[PDB]
Figure 1 (tube, rainbow, N blue to C red):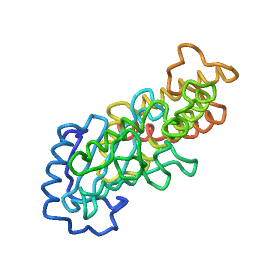
Figure 2 (spheres, rainbow, N blue to C red):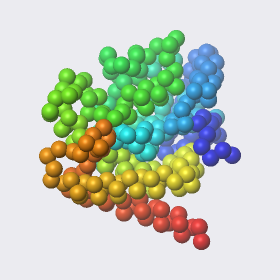
Figure 3 (tube, one colour):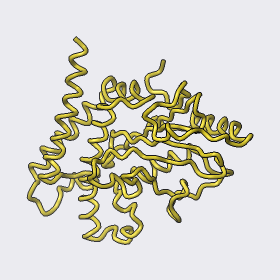
Figure 4 (spheres, rainbow, N blue to C red):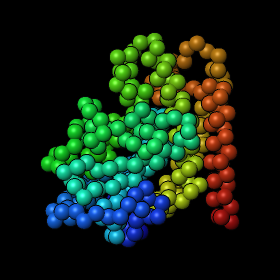
Length: 279
């Protein structure tokens, strides 16, 4: 009944799930009691910006949706991860397959690979970042999901690359952070397009409610169009205006404008179809 429920168990894993064709393993006797604790934590503590779906028929598969936070290149865009808990969960970390709707352009974040890999210590896939290593007694799916939102979908993701952290504040790191954020912003807009063009199993009504009923597609379109005007006004300038400092995405290049307007045609076409169906 609620249009935006943070945690729900649905009847059936969707056929579009990344792990739909991997048959479910047996799991230990303690697995189901552990999932009861995991569900209780998701229901109690997921923020409004993270949806999770579990399934009655596949107790080893989950799908999550994270909305990009405000004043990041990711703002208002949907990030979907398909999850598997293997036979050894929770001894072993959950397995993440990120849906990278990047079309060969590269990564949308240094830790979110185009083939689906998520590099975080809490997923057992990276050594020594600010997310803590996985362990059954400390860790949870909830903690994994808030680590992605809190440590990956950040304001200046270019520094998620460990080598580059030493360059904060420097003239080159500032320039490269802006260049990176311009690209992540344009690519993230394409994530809104993909999530709405191709119905996502178990998340169709939620996405429609967020982008249509609650007005976030209007916001995405308005923000992009306002950014095209400001980018046209400042296309030459050697330095960004003072009020636009501290903005995650202060301006776009000419090629980014064109790229963004390609996506706006598809996003406006989605709004137009919705406005039709309401007549």
